[PDB]
Image (cartoon, rainbow, N blue to C red):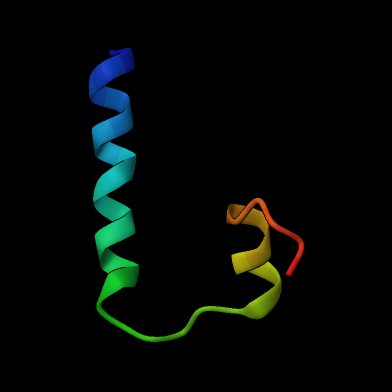
Length: 35
């Protein structure tokens, strides 16, 4: 449930990989450095 749950969500990640619509404010969240 815990290990599988992560996979189900990971799949969504790929969905974004397709398109090239990544906000600058959002990217900062994932990244550690302030930039």
